[PDB]
Image: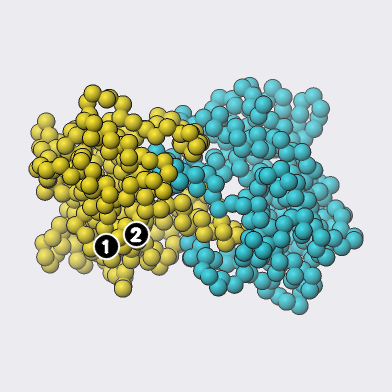
Chain colours: A cyan, B yellow
Amino acid sequence: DPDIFNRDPRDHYDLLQRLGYGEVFKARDKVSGDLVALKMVKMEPDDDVSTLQKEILILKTCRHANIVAYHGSYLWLQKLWICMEFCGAGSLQDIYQVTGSLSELQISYVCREVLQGLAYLHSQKKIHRDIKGANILINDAGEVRLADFGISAQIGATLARRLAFIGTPYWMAPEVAAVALKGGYNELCDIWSLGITAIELAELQPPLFDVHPLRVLFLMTKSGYQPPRLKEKGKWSAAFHNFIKVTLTKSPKKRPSATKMLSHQLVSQPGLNRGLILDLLDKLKNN
Amino acid sequence: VDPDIFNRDPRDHYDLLQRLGGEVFKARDKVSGDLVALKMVKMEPDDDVSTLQKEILILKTCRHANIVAYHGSYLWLQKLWICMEFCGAGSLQDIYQVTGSLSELQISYVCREVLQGLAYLHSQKKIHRDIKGANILINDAGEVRLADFGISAQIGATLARRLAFIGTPYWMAPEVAAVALKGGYNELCDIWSLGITAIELAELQPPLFDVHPLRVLFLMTKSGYQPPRLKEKGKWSAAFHNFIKVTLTKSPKKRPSATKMLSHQLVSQPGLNRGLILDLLDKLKNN
């Protein structure tokens, strides 16, 4: 059961604050008193929430601390509401846009926590598919949670199809259809993405961010494409430089797994705990 | 070769005559008196026309009667104008929405002409990628021209990225970026699309048109997916039914090539010529 309920989510939750496809709200459970996040997305007449059942089930069956918890979905008056774990500090992107770059320690802790999440997903034959700062959520306890990509991706595609930015599948051969579902994704792509995310946390944007997307696609698919590096060498330890080097391995056959990466000096070092992020949150609040 | 993107007002060369439905204009060369189509697209500050050079060159280097001719591109006052051969009757979709379904002969002629275009493209190691009624253009002489997909595809993707309906590639592993560029297209996918198109011309919609796109993606990628068929059996010859059967072959390893298809009874029959479409154009105007 994906538990998509046909009732008003306001039956169970009090909306409290718009956090800012659709809208995100901080809300409180009427019975438990739990804070939750409620993501609302408008539905059009040609929409069908039942097509989201697969991605929803993928998220629902996750049982790990580092994956954002799923509490259920609600369909009501052509709005779809997805109820998930509340992470009061927002995404790391939300945070660094005000605090500035993270320390090496803070990044190291974040990477360890993401890797625990990733090792879990990959053990369940799942792939995150979109590791980046905007998808790493932080709660007020300084704990780190991976946000879901799968549901949002399908909603995004439907919008793009509606506006004819991308094609519809009716004329597509099955090989083409398959790729349009599969994508380029293999589990090890998450490792590369984490590597890019570490740079992003260190530098406030991924490599080539100021370059046109189609141009970057052309560049990154060249043979002899040079994997990105941290810009300021002296600022970062040899271990951090090495973490970047190994996660950003071009050949997926040679790119290390999540569990292998949990063995790396950078994320296995003692001292890494949530207090490092509690520091970041204080800086967020009080500068 | 040079893509001939001119930094000049296209009106230095052409008089606009009328809007056809960015915008498409019927236009006339000031010098030769040649009619042309000018396709206009608005550019954002974010935009870089130079990223379109590859797709523009792919179109420019085509030299075949059944591929729409390319005359040049113009960038002016944040508008991109693409100048192409003029096809006065519009697309077959434009046409059948008024006339109703095409006759088997008319379809047979269109398929033969599309197949000549595809054979040419494939021999040049190009793939059309979007065969459908809307991309098959008809001139006043009843001749058949394949419209370009590649340039429009890139513009569409850029818009989708801008609105975050789809993601950017900055965090993608090279495997993932590569697939996003290759998209699962292979030359034989055009053959499948043509089969769907023949049904579309016969029935005014492709198979499953009333079904949600994501659901059709899921259905069309099962191992036991049943390829579509013509709905009305008695209306169509055994030859047409067989044409559908063989073009809609699931495994690309067994699907017939364009030139193999040109040997098929349906399109190799004597009597196929532009007069069949001249009839359709008379029906469009008068009946």
User: Which amino acid is tagged 2?
Assistant: Lys
Are the residues flagged by discs 2 and 1 in contact, CB closer than 8 Å? yes
Residue labelled with disc 1? B62
Residue labelled with disc 2? B126
Q: How many labels does the image show?
A: 2
Of mark 2 and mark 1, the one earlier in the sequence is 1
Residue at horizontal 60 percent and vertical 40 percent from the top? A151
State the SS at label 2: loop
How far apart marks 2 and 1 lie (CA) works out to 9 Å
Does residue A76 appear in this view? yes
Which circle, 2 or 1, is nearer the viewer? 2
Closer-to-camera residue (A71/A194): A194
Q: How crowded is mark 1: few (under 14 residues within 10 Å), some or many (20 or more)?
A: some
Name the subunit of mark 2.
Answer: B
Q: Residues within 10 Å of mark 2 (few under 14, many from 20)?
A: some
State the SS at label 1: loop
Q: Position of residue A286 (x, y in %)?
A: 81, 56
Q: Position of residue A96 (x, y in %)?
A: 71, 59
Does residue A197 appear in this view? no
Q: Position of residue A195 (x, y in %)?
A: 69, 62
